[PDB]
Length: 121
Image 1 (cartoon, rainbow, N blue to C red):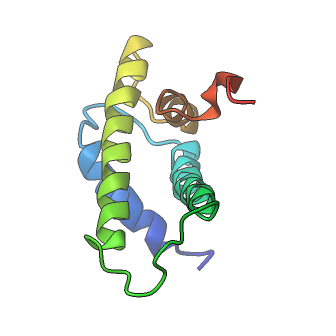
Image 2: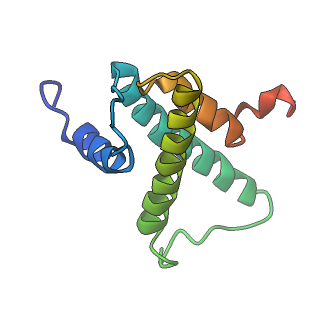
C-alpha cells in the first residue's frame, strides 16, 4: 500500500496519456497530490450536489442504471484531466515552464468554476 500505490499509477497512467505532451514536462509530487485533490474534490462536489437534490428530489439509489455512473464519472474525470493538461500546458507554456504542479491544477479547477472566487457567500 504505502510502499506501492497502484491506483496513483493507474490514474497517472491515464493522465499521462493525456499529458503525453511530456515533450519536456516534469511531474512533481504535487502533481500526484493534484490527483488526490481531484478525486476527493469531485466527490465532495458530487456529494454536495446530491445533497441539494435531497431538498425536494429523491435520488434513485436503487437500480443505479443510467449511462453507467462509473463510466460517466470516469469520462467526466477524463474531461477534467484532459482540460487540465490543456490548461496546465497553457499556464506552464505561459510561464514557458515544463512541469505539472497541483497549483496549476488548482488554477484549472478555479476556472472550472471552483472557489467561485468567493462570489458565492
